[PDB]
Image: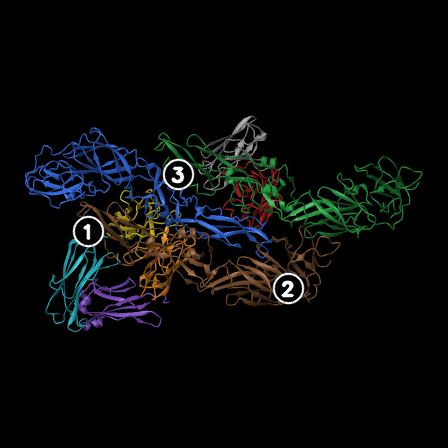
Chain colours: A cyan, B yellow, C red, D purple, F orange, G green, H blue, I brown
Amino acid sequence: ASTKGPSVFPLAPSSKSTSGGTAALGCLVKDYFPEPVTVSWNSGALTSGVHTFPAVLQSSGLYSLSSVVTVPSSSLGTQTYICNVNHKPSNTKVDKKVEPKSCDK
Amino acid sequence: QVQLQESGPGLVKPSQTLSLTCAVSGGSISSGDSYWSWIRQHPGKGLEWIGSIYYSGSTYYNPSLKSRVTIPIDTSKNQFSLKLSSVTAADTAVYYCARHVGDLRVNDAFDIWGQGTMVTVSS
Amino acid sequence: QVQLQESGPGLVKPSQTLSLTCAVSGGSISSGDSYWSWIRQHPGKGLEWIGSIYYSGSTYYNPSLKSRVTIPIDTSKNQFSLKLSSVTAADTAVYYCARHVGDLRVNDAFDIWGQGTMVTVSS
Amino acid sequence: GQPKANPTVTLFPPSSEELQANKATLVCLISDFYPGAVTVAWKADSSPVKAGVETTTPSKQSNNKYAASSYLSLTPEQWKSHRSYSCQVTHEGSTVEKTVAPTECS
Amino acid sequence: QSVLTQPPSVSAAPGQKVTISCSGSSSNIGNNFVSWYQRLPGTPPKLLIYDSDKRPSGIPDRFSGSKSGTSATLGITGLQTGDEGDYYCGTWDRSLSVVVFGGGTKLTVL
Amino acid sequence: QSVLTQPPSVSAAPGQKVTISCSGSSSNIGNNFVSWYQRLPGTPPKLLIYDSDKRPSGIPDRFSGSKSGTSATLGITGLQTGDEGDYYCGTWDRSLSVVVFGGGTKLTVL
Amino acid sequence: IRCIGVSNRDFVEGMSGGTWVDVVLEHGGCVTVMAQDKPTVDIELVTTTVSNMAEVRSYCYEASISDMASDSRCPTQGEAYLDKQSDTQYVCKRTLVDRGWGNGCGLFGKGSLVTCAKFACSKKMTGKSIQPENLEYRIMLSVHGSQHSGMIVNDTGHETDENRAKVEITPNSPRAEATLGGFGSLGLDCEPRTGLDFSDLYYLTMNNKHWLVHKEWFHDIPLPWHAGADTGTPHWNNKEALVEFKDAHAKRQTVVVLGSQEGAVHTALAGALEAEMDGAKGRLSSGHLKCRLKMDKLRLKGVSYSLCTAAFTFTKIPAETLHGTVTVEVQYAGTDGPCKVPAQMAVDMQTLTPVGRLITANPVITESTENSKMMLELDPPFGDSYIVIGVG
Amino acid sequence: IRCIGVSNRDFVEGMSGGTWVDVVLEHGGCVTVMAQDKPTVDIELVTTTVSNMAEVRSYCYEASISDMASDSRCPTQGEAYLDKQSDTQYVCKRTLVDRGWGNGCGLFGKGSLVTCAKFACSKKMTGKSIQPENLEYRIMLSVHGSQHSGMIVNDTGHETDENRAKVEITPNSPRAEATLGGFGSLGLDCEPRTGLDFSDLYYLTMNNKHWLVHKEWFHDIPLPWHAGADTGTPHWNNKEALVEFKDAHAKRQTVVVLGSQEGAVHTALAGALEAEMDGAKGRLSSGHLKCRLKMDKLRLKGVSYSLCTAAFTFTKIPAETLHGTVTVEVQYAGTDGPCKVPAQMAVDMQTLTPVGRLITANPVITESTENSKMMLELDPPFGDSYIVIGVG
Amino acid sequence: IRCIGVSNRDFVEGMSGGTWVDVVLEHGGCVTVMAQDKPTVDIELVTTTVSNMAEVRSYCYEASISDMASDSRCPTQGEAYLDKQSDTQYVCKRTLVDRGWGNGCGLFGKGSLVTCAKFACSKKMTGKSIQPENLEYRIMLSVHGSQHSGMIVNDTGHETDENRAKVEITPNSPRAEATLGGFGSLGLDCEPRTGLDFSDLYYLTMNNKHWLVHKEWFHDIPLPWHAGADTGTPHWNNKEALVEFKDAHAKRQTVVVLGSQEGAVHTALAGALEAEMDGAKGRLSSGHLKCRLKMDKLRLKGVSYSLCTAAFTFTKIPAETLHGTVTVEVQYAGTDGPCKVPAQMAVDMQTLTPVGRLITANPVITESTENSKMMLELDPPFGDSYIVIGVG
């Protein structure tokens, strides 16, 4: 339908997601139109363990594409993870900083 | 082998006119066994035929899409067209441009299918 | 001269089946220009055709009397029949059995009229 | 002679008591598939992530169908920060996808 | 809808020409030619006119048919007491698919 | 009213014969012979069966059509993962005056 | 006695020992049989009922064209393909007409025009097919003897008569025995399977005109042939023979239907025999059967009855009835009851010898009243003679 | 120069005073013309566009029977009259089958059975008819001269070339004049009305297989013939030839449709020429036209241009190109601009006499660069000789 | 009684002393045998099961080319050697095409181009080979006698019938004895080794179309021949005959596959007999065997049973059933049980002599009910006669 950028959800790691010394973080831009949205990790500084899967077309016509990144469990809390989603359609560029699982509330 | 490829603007505005072009390989619109039919295939619903142009250029279509559908044909280009003026949310669907059944097939026979250009109609 | 004479039970019960027989003089049912048509002529209303049998025995009738009317023909006797099963007050009327228009007359041509057997349907 | 029994995908997000432990587990079962073969992919939003995803193989049930289970690992911040979480099961070329959001099933 | 609007009252002077107008529709009266059935008090209708212009054999020359749109016109020139009867128009309907007779014309040659 | 009731869930054992029943009506399924369109995830439906019995050229021999009343039956004998797709019945309606496709058949050769 | 007054009356004398007599049971004729110990019985096959005549392929007798139109294509601009041309109810004819630059085509040449019209048969003559198990010949037998002049043609009552009675012989019942009261029992051995060509002919009906036409002529009628009992939309086999699409010099192919062929059918029905139709049983009044007359059960009734007393008065004195037989109408004035008429026909009255054979042999008065009217029959030689009715 | 490399290349030398030359514009051939004051121009009628080919009566290529049934009547129990037998969409065949007492009839004999089925053509080959006003022959002319080896086959750009260009000659435009820049104007006087039998042939299409079949063979195809542009229910002219109602020994008339006749159509399409179809303009790549070459406007370009300075280097030294013509590929090393190539082909180098005629006569270098690649052409006598390209 | 209603019914009268009778067991015919002390038994070889038909070399019926390419070498620049040219799944054709200086070669001449493509047979007709030990002829015998009109065609139940029963004779079991209850035992001595040329024919199947084609025609089919049961990648024996690599005037060798040869196979299958296939046992309904009828065990059942009491009513009176035999359908009104029908067919009823032979000789009523329907059969002389069914 109309051109619009998706939400930029930051998909952080946690204690129940880290197996061994590695933890999985991610990023998801959802409800996007057109399909051409690219994802980078830390502005291109995080490429090892970065997986950019193909997008999933939702029932509302907004595409949902993202990336995943296997980072260090010791780096969760000392190194910042910030996904960058650049959408060609509508000129959308969003930097979403994923954070550790702060469940103190 | 005869192949059909539907293409066009997959994202359209409400009240707009979507235009899907079905290109044909291995044949033309003036063939001896050709009747290029466009069929609307909405998500969550079955395929419904909307327009079926012939070798002479005119053809018969469904009466529900009679007020908005048009079956253009390019004789020099060897391509077919499915047009939808004043589109809505219900008009967005797959828009394949298959070449239809032969001579004695008074009923339809969708032996060959198009590229399946999906349509999205949102504001 | 060809003459038609409708006769039968002029008084019938409600829900009964009236049977009017049209006898023909000067002709038969197998003629080269014959199509014997029975027409209901109720009082206070115009003549309405109910059944029209042909030389082959079958024929076409009105759709309102399609559920109750029958156009029998006697090939050996040279007579026509108008039957009405499950009759009512609205089915009682004049039941003449005229011989209809000729070959190219796709529309009706009531040149000859029957005897006009009036029907009464009361309980 | 295996009859028609297609696979069904069911997804469940992390619980509130699991998020109180600083963890998140997204379950995704692909059950009743005849035959027992499916490829499981899990991701935050729509792009597939490759960390903390343990997918079981299809095991033949008593009804002649095959079922498998997958667990996508994340945290409470992963469920409360990612706008979507998608799990897709691919069988016979077909794909069955289930998406769950952390702010929509409260 | 199988009704032909005809003038139900018909009088006639000695030698007077009477006019009966049977009004139909575009589908039946306008679609084809309508004839008339002339019935006695103890007799059914006999054919007068075919195709709205062609009178039947044995019909009088004073009976003259005409067709204009869905309206059939029956003129009785030189009408007498023997011209009195029930002259009802009739035509086949293209929409109806059956022949329908009109409202009648109670001719009374007084 | 252009709906063909087809079984939307299709599984398939290795070498298993699957059955898809597309139910129509007396006017369209009972009126004529209905074929099927087999579509991929990125491809539209291709013709399988014509007149409910005559399979198209290049179609597999394991695909077998049948017609009984308004019900079309598609059997897949020796079905594999390549038999998985979207097999939707389709037929022309005498009352509708246009060809209508059915509800689909999500074949999944697991 | 119902057979002596026939102009084509046959006299049967002498059988094969009295057991079996071979006779020709004509449909229009009557045969009178005279035996040695039996009375003269006139058998006339008058009735002929054909029952269950199933319909055959009947040609149309008067057709007519419907609303006709034309589909025209230019010369080298495609052939005419009418929308009503593919309709079975509309007969169409295609032709090559002139289409030019002034004629609307883009090239001067021969365009193609097809004219169609709903050619419907307004009436058709239908020929019933007669199976061999549908014929039933009604033959009336009548013993010549004790009957008056009002019983020769007065056939009202055959079961309660005892002098005449009708018997129906069918193919299922070829052998029968009619008990003629007083005379014994006349045995009929007619062959209903050996009929007068019932399987080679059809009974065509057109305008209530039954005609026993031949099977080859019934199968050779060139009309629009409705096939069987399909009384709806007829097939019209050879339905194109009734109309003619006469093309003009320009694009006008006027389709004109032919006239009524009932006159030409009457012209072709001159060589056939016109038969009657009494409903389900068609009455054919002609034919020729072959009857085995069993005269073994036929006895001479009133042979033991004595002669009459007197008063034989020849009232309505007869003459030769077209064959030499002299029908003697007498009034027996006397109450003798079962008396025998002692009549003689001779020229020489001084000798009193018998001069000629008697048709109604054994003339016996039956009534016991005063004046009993009776009819006798004698066949004297060529010329005139004296008829002495009684003694003195 | 687009015509010298043709294996069926024709050498044109000598015209009717230079005004009109009669040439055969072959659809597959190219003719090179050499004149006294004009350069060698190769004309090749390569394009052949047939536009507005109207459809003709196209037979069915693969039919199939619908739901078939049978109507049976007994022997002497009426003929078969199927309800679908009167339907135009269902083809039916009637026959006389055995019906007996054990066969259900009431008499042992020949009953009548009619088997019908909806015989529909699942696909049909359609033959377009080509009018005489639809042909357009595209003939490319190319002046042999100042061009390199990459311009002999490099036909990308004919309007902006100035050495080669294509001209379309139609029946409406038979006379034309193509202005070949520098060389003047080549006059084409081709007769588009005198074509290669375009009115006696049809363009049949079957499976995207265009074939220029004959008109008699196109009008003699025994398939189910749909008439014209009636794309709905086809007429199926000769539609009964595709199915065969094989009756059994009992009442079973199995109607079996024939197989796919596209293989037999390919077997009958061996003697025809397979044509291409580029949409509305079908591309026929063969034929033979007759062209009037107007060489009056054709001038020798660069005749007033002087000879080249030096550095004629025969790079890619050529040989006889299948006809005795030696294609000389040279690199003019020099900045002479519009210089003329002073080349000679002779055996005797001590005489310096001319040995043979040149195909690309008047060899003139056109480029003003340092090393200019050019192609020349010469036709010496039989054998080998010396090619002196330049002086010294 | 399942053989009298056959139009090609054979009447067998007189054997070689009653021991062995030589008969022609036709696949489409039935032969009725009448003996001196045996009833008329109709034997019809109706079943013909061919079991275990092993596959033969079956040609491809519709092929198609795969992704084709060309390998081109220059004239004197090496021949074409395609990488798919050495692949067995890709059929290739090499040719000499034009390669020039403008054609890309370094010399004007004849280069070599080879065009290859994956020519795969999309479907192939397969011919099963029938061994001599696979045939099994099912012959139904039926004793004409105590049966009604609903048992002439009512073949439902042959083991529990006792008047008719089917026996399967194979090559392994040529001699058999079918115990027909009451009539004794009919001995079949059919020669299954002497069949109707089962080793000279193959059963070709194409589109579910079984055809008993000849062995020479089956071995002469020019299609892409898959060899045996190799159902994977077929060998395609003569696989190059389906495609044609038509080279153009330049380097374009278009490989075009031929059309569907199933229509030409139906055109070549006109002279063969179409056979049915019931799975593993193919049903061939035609042929001609030679049977040894053993009539020694065949006895006249009900000969010691007495005559019927009375009430023989000819309901559904029959006629000649296409051969002169008159099928008499009677209703025995009477409780005689095993009574014998005392019927006679004669012209002369005053003599009571026998006129003609009876087809169903020894007509015996079998049922003990009130009205027993039975079918008899008689063959009188030429003409019509009297049928006296009973006494009085």
Q: Residues within 10 Å of mark 3 (few under 14, many from 20)?
A: many
Q: Residue at x 58, y 66 (%)?
A: I187
Badge nearest the viewer, 3 or 2:
2
Q: In the drawing, what numbered circle is on residue I77? A: 1
Identity, as a three-letter code, of the amino acid under mark 2: Gly
**For the N terminus of chain G, which image quadrant?**
top right
Identity, as a three-letter code, of the amino acid under mark 3: Glu
Badge nearest the viewer, 3 or 1:
1
Identity, as a three-letter code, of the amino acid under mark 1: Gln
Q: Do pointers 2 and 1 mark residues of a single chain? A: yes
Find residue I25 and report its image quarter: bottom right
Judging from the image, what secondary structure is the residue with disc 3 in? loop
Proximity of marks 2 and 1: CB atoms separated by less than 8 Å: no
Q: To which residue does mark 3 refer?
A: G79
Q: In the drawing, what numbered circle is on residue C24? A: none
Marks 3 and 1, Cα distance to the nearest angstrom?
56 Å
Q: Quick one: F27 or I102, which is closer to the camera? A: I102
Proximity of marks 3 and 1: CB atoms separated by less than 8 Å: no
In this orientation, does residue B111 appear? Answer: yes
Please, which chain is the residue tagged with disc 3 on?
G
Q: Quick one: I171 or G363, which is closer to the camera? A: I171
Q: Residue at x 40, y 38 (%)?
A: G80
Marks 2 and 1, Cα distance to the nearest angstrom?
90 Å
Marks 3 and 2, Cα distance to the nearest angstrom?
75 Å
Q: Position of residue I209 (x, y in %)?
A: 43, 56
Q: Do pointers 3 and 2 mark residues of a single chain? A: no
Q: Residues within 10 Å of mark 2 (few under 14, many from 20)?
A: few
Q: To which residue does mark 2 refer?
A: I17
In this orientation, does residue F70 appear? Answer: no
Judging from the image, what secondary structure is the residue with disc 2 in? loop
Mark toward the start of the polypeptide (2 vs 1): 2
